[PDB]
Image 1: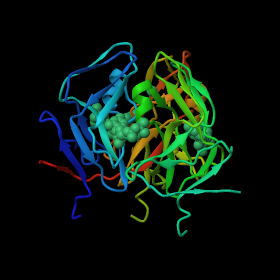
Image 2: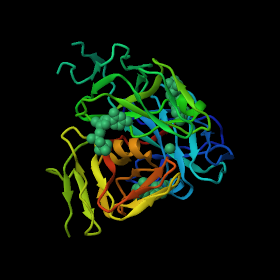
Image 3: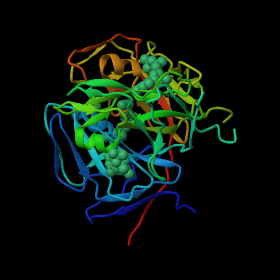
Length: 128
Length: 128
Length: 128
Ligand SMILES: O=c1ccn([C@H]2C[C@H](O)[C@@H](COP(=O)(O)OP(=O)(O)O)O2)c(=O)[nH]1
Ligand SMILES: O=c1ccn([C@H]2C[C@H](O)[C@@H](COP(=O)(O)OP(=O)(O)O)O2)c(=O)[nH]1
Ligand SMILES: O=c1ccn([C@H]2C[C@H](O)[C@@H](COP(=O)(O)OP(=O)(O)O)O2)c(=O)[nH]1
Ligand SMILES: [Mg+2]
């Protein structure tokens, strides 16, 4: 591959932001919003990222929560499992744990992508 | 092993469903319920899967949320860490984020199993 | 490395507990509290662990929920992503899903650390 076994990103909207790690030791690639939305108090919402992704073979893309938002605004990430064979747009489902709404302006880093190494064997069913 | 390093599944109840990936690129193996239960609004519940599993060495089984259920019914997965040395029955703890109960009929895919590769070294305690 | 590619732990407070797996097949290293705190009903809180950690290269440290606490007290773990380049103190953000507060005495195992293998390639942006 030379290195086509990396994170293939395709911006769908011009407004989109290329995912990027914020440190040499960072685990995930920052993931920003492409729209202005409000995560309802005690409610959820799916934020468009405006990008599609192709995870490296042997891994899946887990949308994990950013420490900041979790801490300060009790924001959590629901679902978050992006299959290697997913060609659609990455949507980020946020859940407001707090009693007060949460504002999201375009461009904001609303989550982070982690390329988690998984194993995808077959199922050996044990009879007796 | 030839391939005994795959997902060993043992149905405990005849009603059980063998976990299975739904795509070539899917990350997890579908996980169905073996009973009819209701996930209480704003409450949780542990759904029996009726199966026991033996994860491949070098990984653990993370019970992750299905995108659909998360999106449409604000259903989330609590706990979800199945150790390689777990011989009991896989129980799936679902949490209803919504204001309205959620019905689960036997056979339904209530979560997905992901064989996540972990490293299990020893702890090197740094003194001074 | 010989084996300096293991979980490097540095107790910050004498009161701290060295993370440790509770089984040969356990996926995570137990993580205890270093203080007496209360996880507010329907609220969150960041529990100090009194330790700093250096994850092995090629992985990140995911703070996962303990099955017990999740089941019995509807306790969940928010955020939970500790980067390999994190030199600060591991803080554990717990979220009380239940209607009743949750007490945490010093020494208690409040979560578990899982050294999850990730891949950290570069981003190949697909133009046209
Ligand atoms: O539950 C958690 C989650 C994260 N961290 C630490 C690990 C990581 O190295 C650091 C990340 O801070 P940040 O990512 O630089 O700020 P942000 O999450 O807003 O990007 O916080 C914790 O101690 N506990
Ligand atoms: O937060 C999420 C979770 C999943 N997906 C995408 C990735 C995956 O490829 C697809 C999965 O749809 P599905 O699994 O086929 O439907 P279901 O989750 O009900 O099995 O949804 C997102 O965009 N955002
Ligand atoms: O959603 C879950 C989470 C865990 N387990 C199983 C897998 C694991 O092998 C066992 C762990 O029990 P424990 O870790 O020994 O008790 P505790 O979580 O309090 O440490 O529970 C489940 O069946 N379902
Ligand atoms: Mg939650």
